[PDB]
Amino acid sequence: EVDPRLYFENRSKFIQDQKDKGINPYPHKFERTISIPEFIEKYKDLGNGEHLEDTILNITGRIMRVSASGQKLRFFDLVGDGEKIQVLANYSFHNHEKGNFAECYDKIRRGDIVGIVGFPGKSKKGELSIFPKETILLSACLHMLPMKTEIRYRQRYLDLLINESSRHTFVTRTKIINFLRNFLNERGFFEVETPMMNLIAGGANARPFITHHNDLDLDLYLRIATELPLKMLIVGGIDKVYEIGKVFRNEGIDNTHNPEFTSCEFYWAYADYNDLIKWSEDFFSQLVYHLFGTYKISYNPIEIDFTPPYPKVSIVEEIEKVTNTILEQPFDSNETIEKMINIIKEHKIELPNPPTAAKLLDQLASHFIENKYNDKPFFIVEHPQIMSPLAKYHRTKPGLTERLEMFICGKEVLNAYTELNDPFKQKEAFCTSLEYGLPPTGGLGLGIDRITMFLTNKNSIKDVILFPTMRP
Amino acid sequence: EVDPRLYFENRSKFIQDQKDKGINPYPHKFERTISIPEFIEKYKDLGEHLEDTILNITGRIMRVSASGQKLRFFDLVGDGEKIQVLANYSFHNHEKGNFAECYDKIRRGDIVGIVGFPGKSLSIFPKETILLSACLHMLPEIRYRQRYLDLLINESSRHTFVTRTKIINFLRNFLNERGFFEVETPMMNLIAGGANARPFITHHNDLDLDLYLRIATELPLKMLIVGGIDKVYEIGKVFRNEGIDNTHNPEFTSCEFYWAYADYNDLIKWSEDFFSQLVYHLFGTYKISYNKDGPENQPIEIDFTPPYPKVSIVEEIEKVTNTILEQPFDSNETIEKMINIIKEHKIELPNPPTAAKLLDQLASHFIENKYNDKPFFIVEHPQIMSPLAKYHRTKPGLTERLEMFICGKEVLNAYTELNDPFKQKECFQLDSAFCTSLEYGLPPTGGLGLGIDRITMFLTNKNSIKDVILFPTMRP
Ligand SMILES: C[C@@H]1CCC[C@@H](C[C@H]2Cc3cc(O)cc(O)c3C(=O)O2)O1
Ligand SMILES: C[C@@H]1CCC[C@@H](C[C@H]2Cc3cc(O)cc(O)c3C(=O)O2)O1
Ligand SMILES: N[C@@H](CCCC[NH3+])C(=O)O
Ligand SMILES: N[C@@H](CCCC[NH3+])C(=O)O
Ligand SMILES: [Cl-]
Ligand SMILES: [Cl-]
Ligand SMILES: [Cl-]
Ligand SMILES: [Cl-]
Ligand SMILES: [Cl-]
């Protein structure tokens, strides 16, 4: 046992003493000639007890175990890029003209970043190793590191160094985003950037963040979505367009909500809801196979089968069906509002404030549909116009829209529709752009963080964001 | 020849009349079988007709002409390309509507679907033409507020934003080929560091908390180096709550990377490789022309062939002003001296006149416009300007820093990172989370920032940042 403060204070005095004796504990440059992954790839085939003594290399990394088998034989584990080798430092092999062996190695502690000049071999036990001639401290770790709560979210660097799975999680994340980018680019889509701060915040229903620009003396809204300006680009003649990036919604933090999250929205001119469904099934099934070489995955446990096609459940037909009720249109008539309210009560669930037709329908949809399936993803489709102000009216079903929303394990990860392009039907900047002619178009949104949760077996969004937002 | 409101209001009545006569003017779906680029590629080689092929094609009408009632000529555009629609009474399927009625209805800007056959006279010959989405206004500062108009009317506008995405694509593949790992860091933090700039503030309601939009990505990326991600980067927006002018937009796109075990010399090689390769990739040459002073007056050449000149900020200021600037730079004798030089040359005195801002001002007057024919680096900036850069390995008072300039504008800032936590407190309000991460061991590291919008300005021949942002931030 050691007191952390003593540890820290002592390592601090050590640093100052090195400085004072003229040794620079933070040297500027150490020219490494090979990485640890490279080193392993290149020498893993060596024979037990075989040294290549005439092959000198410079290698770096973080010391993670310190050991000894006497004062003239020190062992360390050295990690870089998520791989590990042994450092076997033997007194006889040490270049004594550069410091007392014992001084130079007593000072090396767990967490230290080091540079090593030495030669590759395997120990007789077969352990792939570097045998120093010289070991340089490049950057000390001044605190004792954990061997094994909230710290993983506040000190993500600690998490990344100690837990192999943490690194796997964020690697998978970037892979997911890479796949998506190439998937859209293969299909002729054009990546763009739209503003994060606008005079209005539209394209979804969510409270916004507000901020103030000093030069223009103006209160701007951080964006809750990217829909409106992307559509303006369709009008502008960019027929396949998308954006991957953050959006901001000013509401509660939970296991599936972070106030900044990463979305992808695309707009596809001359497509419609049917094209969007096909796209969703292709994307998800191909994404999953690309990561796992199979369509069925384990999640915390339950199997999720991503083999297309997926079930499509019509929001009205299904609510009515599981509640032996008819919901007469208009959906915001008093008779249908009262009725919807009755169901809420009849089933003792939380009444939304205020109880508008759109929010009641939404609430009924979360209770009676959204957890219909767990074995596969599925779509809820054909949402009422009152919920869907920017979706186009259904081509055979008055009151409804050509909309879909994909769910995985009761959580929405996708929202898409045929875009309303008739400016007259919309009144009930962007609006001006519609008057110039928005071609028939299909639009689609993904929630990236939520997708990554499922494909890395996490059940908090916090586990797939490097630095999630938290109370200090 | 027409009032815009009449035009608009009339096209509106037309839309309603179509609806009332049972025609849906905004059909849900027209299944096209070929795009315009595809169409061109496939039939460029056809003076002849091929009635041996019936196709469905879409696009926006952009010119309407005629040579008789029975002979109508349109330009149709999609994905940057254009073909002719030659609509001839002969070829029209009269079992689907009066030829003259249909085609009198079609105006400039209309989005249409066409069923016809390919030929040259390079054209599509309709048997039938469907309206898919009308343009209710006659088509021609507006370029910034209605960027859709700009994208449709000016070929160069589309070139500009295509080039922009290409630039970002090249950069992404350039870092990925070299083993770099893309990540996302937060846009809203409890403090905003990594640069000197006023921040935007916003408030989260459920946690009842004030947060700062990020002015840079430096600190959290460095925390990822500590975490063992030795090559890391982020491309994305940052926010600085400052003035707006030809080279400043309050949100702009940057790229920052951190390269463990590299230093300032690695960063210079990287900069030269990146820029020269980027330019050749776009133009098949290293020398490009740029209308600094506007398309009105004469352009200049910019030669991106490496290597680029490196000018040491202290050496050069002293040299062009016959002065010695004794360290410390924030002593009174050296502040007063710097002031007197600003006074003797009638340049604007910064408020307050700190050592760092005076040095900065002297650097913008006497160095930053040294070259115009090539990019160049200003290097080895004083510590007082550079609170996160590491101290120079042989030059007291200075740091291992570089800034690249193109035509007098900074596009790159990079350095060997200060990784000694004891020296940093002394340099520094900035993060304790960050400061704590340093104590766990930041390896020797090189960091670099690019200003993407400003790079794109130079490589698309624009001299306002507003020309390379789709929707720049403006007053209503
Ligand atoms: C833009 C996407 C398209 C798919 C449907 C939803 C999913 C989105 C909802 C959401 C809301 C929120 O307040 C905080 C979040 O973190 C998330 C999220 O992670 O996922 O929005
Ligand atoms: C992160 C980069 C590294 C290179 C140096 C600067 C360039 C950056 C500075 C700037 C500041 C600003 O308030 C508004 C801007 O638009 C820009 C810009 O576009 O250029 O920052
Ligand atoms: N803006 C939508 C995503 C696209 C919906 C289809 N246009 C949302 O945030 O849910
Ligand atoms: N954060 C710097 C970019 C360079 C980073 C070098 N450590 C800036 O905003 O200007
Ligand atoms: Cl249908
Ligand atoms: Cl939700
Ligand atoms: Cl390297
Ligand atoms: Cl050097
Ligand atoms: Cl600047």
Image (cartoon, coloured by chain):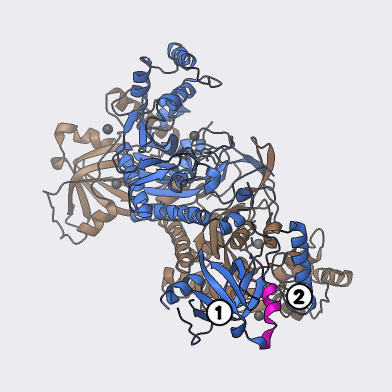
Chain colours: A brown, B blue
In the picture, measured across the screen, residue B304 lies left or right of residue A210, that is left
Task: For mark 1, name the chain.
Answer: B
* Region in magenta: B95-107
Q: Residue A153: which numbered mark, if any?
A: none
Quick one: B77 or A259, which is closer to the camera?
A: B77
Q: Is mark 2 within 8 Å of ligand 5?
A: no
Q: Residue at x 40, y 17 (%)?
A: B328
Q: Who is closer to the viewer here, A297 or A174?
A: A174
Name above or below for residue B468 compared with residue B33: above
Are the two marked residues, 1 and 2, in contact with CB atoms closer than 8 angstroms? no
Image coords of residue B10 (percent x, y): 77, 65
Looking at the rendering, which quadrant does residue A103 occupy? top left
Residue closest to the far right: A334
Describe the element under mark 2 as helix, strand or loop: helix
Q: Which mark is residue B18?
A: 2
- Furthest toward the top, the residue is B333
> What amino acid is at disc 2?
Gln
Choose the circle earlier in sequence order: 1 or 2.
Answer: 2
List x then y, in percent, for residue B243.
Answer: 59, 35
